[PDB]
Structure formats: C-alpha cells, structure tokens
Image 1 (cartoon, helix red, strand yellow):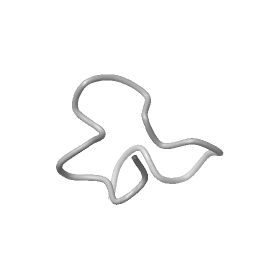
Image 2 (cartoon, helix red, strand yellow):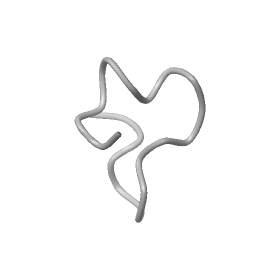
Image 3 (tube, one colour):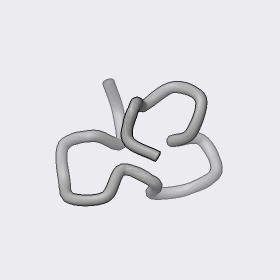
Image 4 (cartoon, one colour):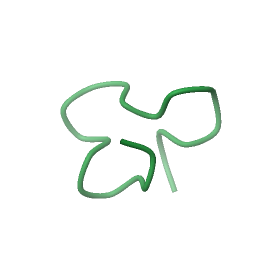
Length: 22
C-alpha cells in the first residue's frame, strides 16, 4: 500500500490505480 495510511488517500495523481483509497 502507499497513500492509504492517513485520512483521504488521494495524495497525488498516483494514488488512484494502486492505493485502494480514491
């Protein structure tokens, strides 16, 4: 996982098709 240990998950244009948080 990557952008999924905070509150939203959509931190940039990469946390969409990899981190299930967007």
